[PDB]
Length: 48
Length: 48
Length: 42
Image (tube, rainbow over the protein chains, first blue to last red):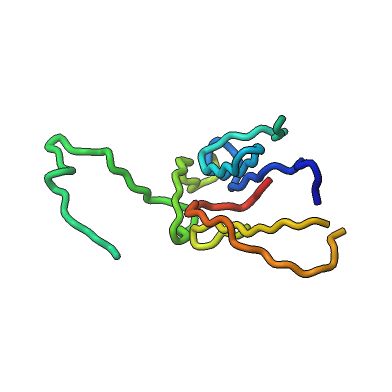
């Protein structure tokens, strides 16, 4: 239940670290980017 | 379909090739159509 | 979101409006051959 598009995307994986696989789905107002790579996260994931 | 053929003249070197690797140890059996590329040592004991 | 046999499936729907009492369906929109192990999400 949303207005003004606050919710953006999702992350899927096993441990969400630079070691094992990770899926990112991002929706940065232009296109639906789906990216499965070996990806690193921080403890406060946010977008401007 | 499964296709198999011979590549002796394309993957054999007199000095020996070591570019091709396999895995021998894992904790649990593999799910169908699954790929794992971990490198963690097989924990056979208690001390890491 | 579903993940079976190495395939990742995503169904979606949008509508205008606690959750409301009503009936609606969802249409398939994404299928991908990801084929990995997924346990936790964010």
